[PDB]
Amino acid sequence: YVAHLASDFGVRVFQQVAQASKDRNVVFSPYGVASVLAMLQLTTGGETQQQIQAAMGFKIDDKGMAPALRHLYKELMGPWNKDEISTTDAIFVQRDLKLVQGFMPHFFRLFRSTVKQVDFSEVERARFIINDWVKTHTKGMISHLLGTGAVDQLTRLVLVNALYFNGQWKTPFPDSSTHRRLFHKSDGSTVSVPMMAQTNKFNYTEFTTPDGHYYDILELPYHGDTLSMFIAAPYEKEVPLSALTNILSAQLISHWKGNMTRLPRLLVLPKFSLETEVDLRKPLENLGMTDMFRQFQADFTSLSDQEPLHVALALQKVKIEVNESGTVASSSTAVIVSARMAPEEIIIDRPFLFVVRHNPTGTVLFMGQVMEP
Image 1 (spheres, one colour):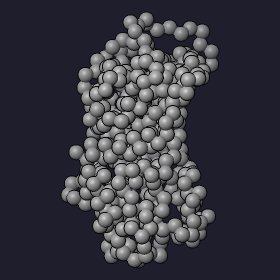
Image 2 (cartoon, one colour):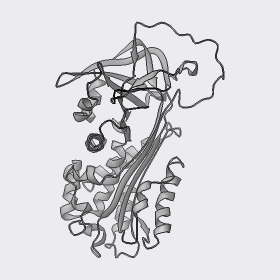
Image 3 (spheres, helix red, strand yellow):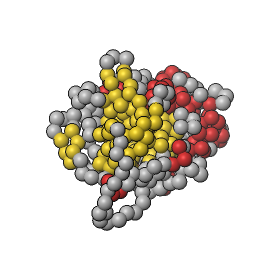
Image 4 (cartoon, rainbow, N blue to C red):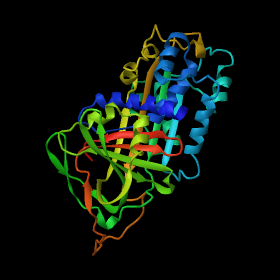
């Protein structure tokens, strides 16, 4: 119920970063931003608090919620994970602050985590403590956040979410296939980028936005069908990849997955490894949560009814990778390159949209748009 609410909140946050970057590559995690804020919730009280809550659709402290999230987090970092995905949250607050009695223990009760205490007077040190955290929890795949570049002696409250993903395909793409096809930018131009391709009966479906926009929706299962990569791209050119993401919801995906059908086709999908770091500040304000960032309006009295606090910096960084398989070796010169001929073929040579979801719960782990691989 929670994963479903957390999923939408994160998509709603994605729409923001998207609509804020026309014609631009962006990888983002609806789940991640959903988690951090679920925690930031406990620190916030009164005014500011409701903004977050209303915007998220649920109060973390209501019975059942928090534990639900703990559950989902665990099942994600489960056994199947197989080093394919990392995730992490973290709130840093000025140590010396008279935190409200029994807050930390409560926090740890619900999130099995602790609100990190650093001395922002040591700008060089703190700036590091933060980065070092993102490093030690993302398997080193994410060792530095550019945002910290702005932490200074006046910093009081910092929020962070970092994830790294590079799943292992259920059915890996033959290496002896990744040729160097051409890609059309929204720009109008083009570029020859590598594009792997495999022929199989991919779970396919054509979709139509409630306004005359027709996209192709494919589903690429990762090992054990635990996770799935959904790729959606319009038929014609011109058609704004925009249209979809605007009414893109946790429900919608379950709907594409609704009337799909395994069909024989040659899939040509560009390889791509993207990196994104968003300053959740404007995107979150656009969703109503504005008090948290305003100095004499923010209310974190639930955390420290002492000195005036406020989120001085909240951000997310996500490295996503799509390659032949989950990553294996290969021959250095393949003479042949065969495959059963298929009826139709799908060439993803225009900007497309992707979505990684945790099929069991439905969680929208990652989302993003590849405008130029």
